[PDB]
Length: 292
Ligand SMILES: COCCCN1CCc2c(Cc3ccc(Cl)cc3)[nH]c3c(OC(F)F)ccc(c23)C1=O
Ligand SMILES: [Mg+2]
Ligand SMILES: [Zn+2]
Image 1: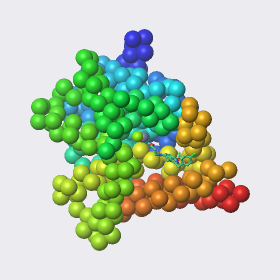
Image 2: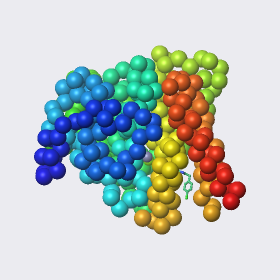
Image 3: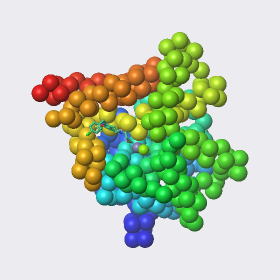
């Protein structure tokens, strides 16, 4: 409660001051408190606080709840990865001009889902517990928090706005299962290959939203080389140390998973090119190392 007090008081610097509009944004120099402020600025500049009447104290308390329910002891899947996925959503909406293409409820759900999509993750090598099992648990945690007293940032919504928002949130979190991404991306590319991609179709809109969640989830792969190398470290710590081969593994994951995604995304809105570009520059660098 010491921490909610300092955060509820602080001034929220502008989007420009915080750099949360650059696809190149990094979080390494920021304290937890500063990522909270960045997160309030994301909600605010998306018009989410205005259009849905979010009480300042509840947003603050919601954000600290979410941060609280990521595990510090997990190297990569932690609050900072959740914060970075949201920042990328923000930059894709603003810098990448995708805001125009969506409604406010879609935007409000993508931001909440980006921040919540890995809640209570314990590291890839602790697949304990008791078709997207993890993602279902992530959404449960997310809903559980959205309902906690004092944390209900969706109280300003009507019952029908609320039910619509939770549907998207759930779809968005579940979309972060790379299995679903592999299952559904073929249709997405096909409709962009043939120039028939239209967002006004509901099934197509929902598919874009799933694809955008993956693009943000994986976006460490697009970052300036010294930033991406540091994350790549964290990914390796989690995968190996449960807390020479790597460069070529990196190139395989970029080719199998990332490049097409970011290519397709650039066709939808070419202001998302920094992501595709950042991904290529990283493939180049990793391949050079892969060749020793
Ligand atoms: C949400 O995550 C759920 C799991 C999906 N996954 C794992 C796969 C992955 C690789 C490929 C890799 C290479 C070497 C090792 Cl030892 C381990 C993995 N690279 C990563 C990455 O790179 C960029 F940070 F540097 C950023 C994110 C991810 C990965 C990522 O998303
Ligand atoms: Mg995940
Ligand atoms: Zn993730």
